[PDB]
Amino acid sequence: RLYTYKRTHAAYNLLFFASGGGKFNYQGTKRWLEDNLDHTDSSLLQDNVAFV
Amino acid sequence: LTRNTRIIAEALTRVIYNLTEKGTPPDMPVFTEQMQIQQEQLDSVMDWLTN
Amino acid sequence: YGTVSSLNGEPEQGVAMEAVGQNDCSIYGEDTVTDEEGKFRLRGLLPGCVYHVQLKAEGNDHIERALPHHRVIEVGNNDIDDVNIIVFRQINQFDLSGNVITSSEYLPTLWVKLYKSENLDNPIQTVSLGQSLFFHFPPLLRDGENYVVLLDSTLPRSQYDYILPQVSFTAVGYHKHITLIFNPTR
Image (tube, rainbow over all chains, first blue to last red):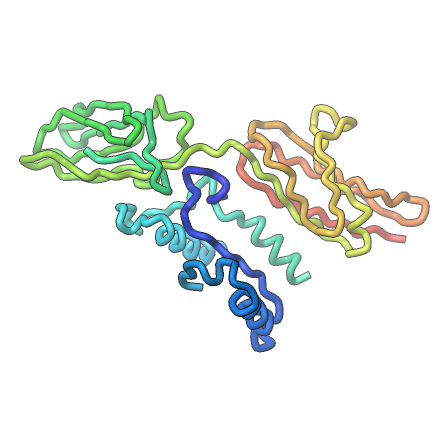
């Protein structure tokens, strides 16, 4: 709702991640964070990542 | 759940929009109407999740 | 002497701006339609009374909220400066939603409806549930408009027993989470 409207379109890329593999040592996050960092060079997980 | 969502979302909104150095004292909220955290939606989603 | 900007920073234009006084000064106060930058030029600078910058009732139909509704400012022996207020526009859509409670196998054989109240034989939306227990009817306008959410399944009574739910949600609010429960028998 906030991003849909121009006047409230803040300049902050937001990567939401409904991760799987949670209480299991957070494997879903491990694999996801690995794929967006070392596998590729694109993706926002390198651009200007603020607090996660 | 609604209160926690209000707290987190309002903090995020203030930090994102540079509001702190824009006035907006923390003694009044953003999410009053037209953006109220849908209690029904939260309850139904939680119920479905527990289903 | 400030600015009327949007949430992101967009300077609002054409917003009526005024200051209503209090105490004996309740009778003093003028208005000024803001410019593109949001720079209002309120005048009538009488000290000895606190001021309240707030949104004119008239001329501000399109705009829904002003987050700092009023800003208390002490009027001393000088002028005021740097008065920034953020404002919200008036979203008019309804943004319907709503989950469905049913077994997984019945989900593909379901299409939620949006039967208008005035005519229950001419649906206006037939969002199929498909494989997701969540319909997200495209945002509608909110003005009365009693509707129906008749859950039109494809499953006939010849091999199963069921009752299709029906929900009326007269559109005056801003969201909805219809929670249809579908448990057929036989």
